[PDB]
View: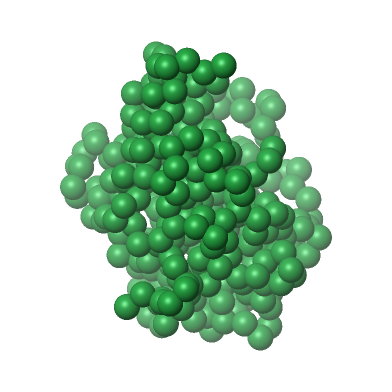
Length: 345
Ligand SMILES: OCc1cn(-c2ccc(Cl)c(C(F)(F)F)c2)nn1
Ligand SMILES: *[C@@H]1O[C@H](CO)[C@@H](O)[C@H](O)[C@H]1NC(C)=O
């Protein structure tokens, strides 16, 4: 229980229900590395389905019941045994309480039952951390899982621009997007519509270069990794199971026959294709969901390299490829669990 809760001092930056947003922090006095992690957990895109989420997922919509501390796990652990990559970093966990894939910039008001302020929560956390040590940082890694992974892609360049404009051009902003790289593909039995309605309901914002390509009405495109990633300037490491459970869910996939076998194999092939030109990526051939804040995140390997090792090699590459220190690790085998190191479940 080593990360301590701080509610935002700017109380106009709120969770869905108007309660203040916040962050959990464990400082590491010696370190100039900062890890800011965006929690995930789907989203809601109209009054009805947000009302339902408020009944049974209220911690994702409100800070009123948050605990005063959280234990850092996986990449947020301070133990080198659990976190070979960044155990000595300053650790920040940002709870997801905006239900907007971290894209929203809209307040609760007479016109809005809910506030959707995810993009502003990130900006405010960064602003308040600069007075707590972030001003002395050399690397700010914006990480995230699930909706938080997509949130990394939507916000990493805005964090970089924010620090540049505040007068901190020496902080290197990087992104780590875990399980947030989705395909706008055809369902197996009859995602783009959800995001389309979400953006209007949230007043959602997307990165500028991507917005300029797709333009008004088509900004939903920028929520899909393979479309937004080529527009980004900050270095982004992409972690994505080839057969992500959430992708299969939105594809309406739940003794597998030929049609479904071909569907699943084509999904893995398409995911692999979208990662071909992503130099820093870790994509195992597993049916699973999220990775980087679980305690046993060290166990999975691609081509004999673990994710903590891949991320360390990424660090080195950002100091020609490195001998025995790869950063591009995408499985080529075509079926869930053809990789023996996949999570057991
Ligand atoms: O916790 C599971 C989960 C999945 N998602 C998510 C994020 C972005 C997109 Cl773009 C999509 C989809 F389905 F639209 F592709 C889903 N968010 N949280
Ligand atoms: C507080 O947040 C709002 C955005 O919701 C912003 O307009 C305002 O300037 C902030 N001001 C502070 C913290 O001084």
